[PDB]
Image (tube, rainbow over the protein chains, first blue to last red):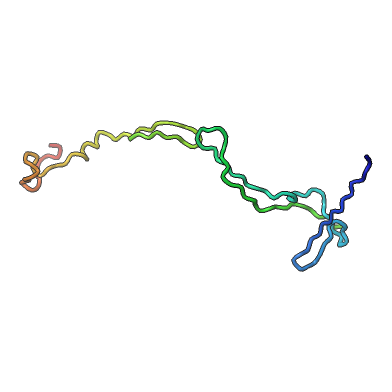
Amino acid sequence: ASRLLDPDTLVELEGVNGEWFDLTNGTEGIYLATEVTGLLDPPVKATYEEPGNFPGARYLNHRVLRRDLVFGVEIL
Amino acid sequence: HYDIVRTKEGDVYMEVVFKHDYEELKHIYVWANPFLRPEFQFPKLWVMFGPAKW
């Protein structure tokens, strides 16, 4: 009926020097900003051919591509 | 020759290629003696002196 949606989601970066950032709690002064693109499923190139005059297409391949993540961080 | 072409975008056409009537002179050979059997060709060269057109 009535509820607050307050997830337990923790986001951390471990850097190339072993330095850590908590992007949920911002204890290092840095937070994940709004509008993230590239979490959840990775991009896929599905390949189909439409040769000749038969109705529709044949599947040939699918490949998982390089994942691009676009995000921002709010630095106080 | 002629080509009947069906392209991947769906165009179908015929192309017909022709050679000019000059091509006859490439399929005619100047025999050493036109008036003799190929089994006996004397004199060994066809040779003619005169005005170039004639």
